């Protein structure tokens, strides 16, 4: 439980730096902009996760069905295995049945 | 391609005549349509045998 | 071998019909009120009661019925701009002869909404046609 | 010449409009250059911090993808075997040394993979949120309408000191109609500033509205906004996407 | 290019108010005063602007933007300007409030 | 307006710094830590449940499962192929003309009912159109041209009495789709196909002047229609003499999906231009 003896340099953060000032800027783009582009397109991320949501099982099964054949051998394997495990666990376990 | 014509299609530089079935496509659509969908008169006559048999 | 086609613009006013409205028609002014389906417009002036009821985006009176747990019956008055407390006074005082006792009330001041135990939907509809909201 | 702006849209019968000073940006000392009627249904709406909150969060989250993966006892390097036998050793029994119990072994639950929180606050809600935000920036007196936005010069000190003369508070969000039409002195002076910001009204947003101690709206901008928002109390439920052809609609 | 030194906004109404304002009624509306000078409506945009502008410079004081939906009669503007406002803080006021000797406030900012 | 407004002059800025969501919005999650919710964490003691494996849902502990003792039956039998018709009450109709959503002036078929959002059709779900009921029978004052897929006697009556003309027209799954959300079909940019003929079993329903079936012989239209009045006891109006006559007369081909268009055509909505085939085989195809 021995704890840090010397004060760290206080991290100074300008909340006024570019990215933070400009946060959430185009959020209303569809509405204010006579909808053409959806808020979705403001999402920069992993191919299969854009404008979508799900629990682990759905995520995984999705990554598979989308990028599956572009994955490395080993990751792929671990993915199929995680899938199986999850199948078994969500369907076949719980308190609530 | 079809969809792209629908969007703009003037500017899309899509060949218009291509938006209709080919001679093959045409004769096949023809073949199936006359196959599974009989004539109105012909359907009435299909019904007369039934109604009279049940009578 | 692409079949030949013909480009003419005069049949386009047929296609014009098929486009749906993205905004609701203001309802046709008639000679006779109420209408066959029972629709009454709000007045030319508005009353001086220190509260008001916006009609629905359908120009219907914003009184609805709602249940909870299948057995709890409720009636919701919506879109009310003014002192709702007054509206509460007047509503419960309208209903009290009907039930012999004041009906239970929940006022939501921030929501601009009123809530009342039981189904008064029909009678509140009328009573807001009275005051012409 | 007094600039006096009438609302381009019908007010409901029981409700009078609002009025804001039109300030201009060329002189420090030209404070009220004119008068504008604002629509009650946008800038007078019943203030609801509830929805402010809701949508403010929805702004924060819905973009969020957290990439944090931890490795389950399946994904760790090795230890595909029972370290020693079930019985007789006289110590606690284990499967793989990658049992989460073990030191260098797996993580039981933890984070999983790229993980997204994405959800769509319903339409008319986000809409009514901008509504409220504006109403609030106005009612707390910190909204300033401008005409023009033509700036005397590209010196940013001028701008800072202008905010100083008008007691504008620390931060400011400047809103203009389009990206192309912003005059060159605005762009110049502001792009070299931290606190002030310059944005097309297509990117007006709640979070930013609250993030800046003062909102400043151009007249064409307001005439635009008022309309775009007011559209929604009067609108049908979409049949198909609105981006498509509609009778009345663009 | 210069920057004007700020006003303190601290306000007390002068005793000549009524006369200033009525002078501004007659000059802004250009009207010979209908018998009630303070009950005439401000609804017209031009007249309202001219009125509150001249009133802005003369009294060295302006109306907050919210309050501008709230001015209709001239009586409203009257009662508005009748009210003083202190820009001093609760603290600055605490200093000037005649403090008992056993209380010493230091300001560490 | 909302005096709440004037309370905000008093208060400090609304900013991110101060925000509370509506009380009772977030009902807080709890976590199995601590003395109360730790230690068996509401999972019980031992047995099956504590280990998370309790058997599947239909299960009775091996006694022959409730849902499985009961014999099968034709119930949901052929449920997929049983036609559905979305109901439309007359009361709703009167409503929709009253608020001027659908206007009686120009002809009324399904499409218009749709665009007023007065009805909703999900063709993929085996919905074969709108059908008519008599609910506002006495309420109904409007003079209207209506084309539906099904209607009931009393309904036909209540439109007749006011002097409108009702026609029973059929649509197949595909054509019905094209009907309901037409603009997105155009943006599909495919030609506008032939209409199907109703199936064999349905044939008798559409060949009767009894229903004023669109495929029925017009020679019985004036007959059976007048008959409707003697049964329900009112004076039958003369439609031929009316001003709005030429709209009420307006029909479709049994091969036509819309009003004013024809099978084989193609709509370019960018150029606002219609395209028709000049090729013969095509015209023989789509005009047959
Ligand atoms: Mg999960
Ligand atoms: Mg409910
Ligand atoms: Mg292993
Ligand atoms: Mg092994
Ligand atoms: Mg093992
Ligand atoms: Mg290690
Ligand atoms: Mg590790
Ligand atoms: Mg316990
Ligand atoms: Mg135990
Ligand atoms: Mg046990
Ligand atoms: Mg349905």
Image: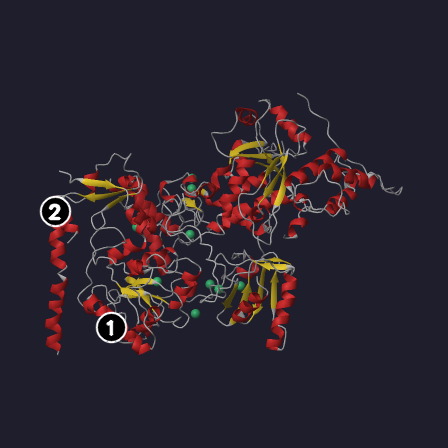
**Structure colour scheme:** secondary structure
Residue with the mark numbered 2: F281
Mark found first going from the N terminus, 2 or 1 = 1
Along the line of sight, the residue nearer the viewer: D83 or E49: E49
Along the line of sight, the residue nearer the viewer: E87 or D248: D248
Decide: few, some or many residues near mark 2? Use Cα within 10 Å; few <14, some 14-19, many ≥20.
some
Q: Are marks 2 and 1 in contact (CB under 8 Å)?
A: no
Q: Position of residue C58 (x, y in %)?
A: 47, 58
* Cα distance between the residues tagged 2 and 1: 41 Å
Q: Quadrant of the C terminus of chain A?
A: bottom left
Decide: few, some or many residues near mark 1? Use Cα within 10 Å; few <14, some 14-19, many ≥20.
some
* Mark 2 on the same chain as mark 1: yes
Q: Position of residue C67 (x, y in %)?
A: 50, 68
Tell me the number on the disc at residue C108. Answer: none
Residue at (50% x, 72% y) in the render: C71
Of all residues shown, which one is farthest toward the top? Answer: E1
Which chain letter matches label 2? F
Residue F226 seen? yes
Along the line of sight, the residue nearer the viewer: D29 or D68: D29
Tell me which corner region of the image, top left, top right, bottom left or bottom right, holds residue E2: top right
Q: Is residue C36 above or below residue A39?
A: below
Badge 2 marks a residue whose secondary structure is helix
Ligand 11 lies under 8 Å from the Cβ of mark 2: no
Q: Quadrant of the N terminus of chain A?
A: top right
Tell me which corner region of the image, top left, top right, bottom left or bottom right, holds residue D88: bottom left
Q: Is residue D196 above or below residue D103?
A: above
Q: Position of residue C31 (x, y in %)?
A: 48, 62
Residue with the mark numbered 1: F224
Badge 1 marks a residue whose secondary structure is helix
Q: Is residue E92 above or below residue C29?
A: above
Is E78 on the left or on the right of F226, as rendered? Answer: right
Q: Is residue F260 above or below residue D147?
A: below
């Amino acid at each position: 439980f021995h704890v840090r003896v010397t004060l760290p340099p206080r991290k100074v953060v300008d909340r006024w730096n570019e990215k933070r000032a400009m946060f959430g800027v185009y959020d209303n783009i569809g509405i204010l902009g006579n909808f053409e582009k959806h808020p979705k397109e403001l999402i920069k991320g992993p191919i299969w996760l854009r404008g979508w949501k799900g629990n682990e099982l759905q995520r995984c099964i999705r990554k598979k069905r989308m990028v599956g054949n572009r994955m490395f051998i080993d990751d792929l394997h671990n993915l199929n295995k995680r899938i199986s495990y999850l199948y078994k666990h969500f369907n076949r376990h719980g308190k609530y049945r | 391609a079809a969809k792209q014509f629908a969007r703009h299609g003037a500017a899309s530089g899509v060949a218009a005549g291509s938006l209709w079935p080919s001679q093959e496509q045409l004769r096949e659509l023809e073949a199936e349509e006359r196959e599974w969908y009989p004539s109105l008169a012909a359907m009435q006559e299909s019904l007369r045998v039934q109604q009279l048999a049940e009578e | 071998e692409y079949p030949s086609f013909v480009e003419s613009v005069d049949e386009y006013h047929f296609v014009e019909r098929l486009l749906p409205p993205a905004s609701i028609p203001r309802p046709p002014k008639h000679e006779h009120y109420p209408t066959p389906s029972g629709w009454q417009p709000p007045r030319d002036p508005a009353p001086s009661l220190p509260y008001f009821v916006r009609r629905s985006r359908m120009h219907n009176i914003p009184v609805y019925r709602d249940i909870t747990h299948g057995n709890r019956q409720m009636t919701v008055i919506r879109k009310v701009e003014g002192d709702i407390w007054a509206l509460q006074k007047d509503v419960e005082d309208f209903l009290s002869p009907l039930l012999g006792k004041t009906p239970v009330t929940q006022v939501n001041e921030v929501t601009g909404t009123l809530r009342v135990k039981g189904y008064f939907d029909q009678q509140l509809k009328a009573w807001l046609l009275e005051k012409g909201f | 010449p007094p600039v006096l702006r009438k609302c381009e849209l019908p007010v409901p019968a029981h409700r009078r409009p609002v009025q804001a000073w039109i300030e201009s940006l060329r002189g420090y000392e030209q404070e009220r250059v004119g008068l504008t009627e604002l629509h009650p249904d946008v800038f007078s709406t019943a203030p609801r911090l509830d929805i402010l909150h809701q949508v403010a969060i929805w702004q924060k989250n819905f973009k969020r993808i957290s990439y944090a993966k931890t490795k389950t006892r399946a994904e760790v390097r090795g230890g595909g075997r029972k370290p020693w036998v079930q019985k007789g050793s006289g110590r606690a029994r284990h499967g793989s040394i990658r049992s989460p119990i073990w030191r260098g072994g797996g993580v039981a639950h933890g984070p999983r993979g790229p993980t997204s929180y994405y959800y769509m606050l319903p339409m008319k809600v986000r809409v009514q949120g901008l509504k409220v935000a504006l109403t609030v920036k106005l009612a707390q007196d910190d909204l300033h309408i401008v005409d023009s936005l033509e700036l005397p010069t590209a010196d940013p000190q001028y701008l800072i000191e202008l905010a100083r003369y008008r007691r504008w508070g620390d931060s400011v969000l400047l809103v203009d109609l389009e990206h192309e039409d912003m005059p060159q002195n605005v762009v110049a002076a502001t792009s070299g500033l931290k606190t002030f910001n310059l944005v097309p009204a297509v990117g007006l947003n709640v979070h930013s509205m609250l993030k800046h101690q003062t909102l400043v709206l151009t007249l064409p901008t307001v005439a635009f906004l008022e309309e775009k928002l007011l559209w929604h109390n009067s609108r049908y439920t979409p049949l198909y996407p609105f981006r498509l052809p509609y009778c009345d609609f663009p | 290019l210069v920057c004007p030194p700020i006003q303190s906004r601290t306000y007390i109404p002068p005793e000549d108010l009524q006369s200033r304002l009525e002078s501004h009624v007659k000059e802004v509306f250009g009207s010979s005063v209908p018998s009630n000078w303070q009950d005439i409506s401000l609804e017209d945009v031009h007249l309202k602007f001219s009125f509150l502008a001249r009133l802005a410079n003369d009294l060295r004081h302006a109306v907050p933007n919210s309050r501008l939906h709230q001015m209709c009669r001239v009586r409203d503007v009257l009662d508005f300007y009748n009210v003083p406002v202190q820009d001093r803080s609760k603290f600055d006021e605490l200093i000037a409030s005649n403090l008992p000797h056993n209380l010493k406030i230091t300001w560490g900012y | 307006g909302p005096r709440a407004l004037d309370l905000l002059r008093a208060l400090p800025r609304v900013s991110l710094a101060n925000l509370k969501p509506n009380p009772g919005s977030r009902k807080p999650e709890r976590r199995p830590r601590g003395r109360r919710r730790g230690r068996k964490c509401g999972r019980g003691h031992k047995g099956e449940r504590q280990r998370g494996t309790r058997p599947r849902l239909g299960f009775e502990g091996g006694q022959t499962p409730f849902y499985l003792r009961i014999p099968k039956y034709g119930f949901n039998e052929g449920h997929s192929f049983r036609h559905q018709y979305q109901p439309l009450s007359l009361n709703r109709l009167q409503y929709l003309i009253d608020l001027g959503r659908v206007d009686p002036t120009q002809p009324i078929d399904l499409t218009q009912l749709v665009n007023g959002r007065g009805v909703t059709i999900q063709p993929s779900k085996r919905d074969y159109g709108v059908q008519l009921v008599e609910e506002g029978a006495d309420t109904f004052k409007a003079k209207v041209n209506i084309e539906v897929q099904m209607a009931s006697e009393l309904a036909i009556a209540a439109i007749e009495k006011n002097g409108g003309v009702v026609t029973t027209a059929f649509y197949d799954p595909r054509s019905l789709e094209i009907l309901c959300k037409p603009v997105p079909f155009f943006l599909r940019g495919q030609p506008i196909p032939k209409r199907m003929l109703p199936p064999e079993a349905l044939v008798p329903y559409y060949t009767d002047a009894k229903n004023r079936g669109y495929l029925a012989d017009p020679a019985r239209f004036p007959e059976a229609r007048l008959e409707l009045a003697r049964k329900y006891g009112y004076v039958l109006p003369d439609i031929t003499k009316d001003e709005l006559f030429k709209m009420l007369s307006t029909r479709k081909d049994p091969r036509q999906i819309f009003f004013g268009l024809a099978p084989g055509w193609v709509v370019n909505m960018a150029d606002k231009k219609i395209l028709k085939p000049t090729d013969e085989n095509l015209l023989k195809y789509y005009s047959s």
